[PDB]
Length: 127
Image (cartoon, rainbow, N blue to C red; front, side, top):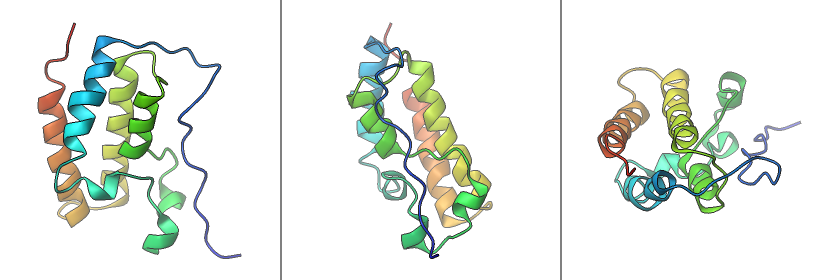
């Protein structure tokens, strides 16, 4: 009975309604893809691997995981109906980090930076 990770969030759901919208195209080509290249992005590029990291309490505490790798796959697979759904997934990811960790932790400074950038990039979206 050693530690395991949960199954990752779904990136495809054939019974969920979806659309391609100008705002969602923008969220992939501009926002995600620019954030993905940032020097602080790496911890957020894949689901939190609590086994590899030796944080057996991670998924004890965080029940709604989200990461940019999943968000990337959702955008590529046209999983979302609108921009707001995806913005919500970005917000879940940031929030989870702030929940599990504490002010001034390196990982938090990273998420804080990314979140400021995020906000500056989604300030104006296409119509």
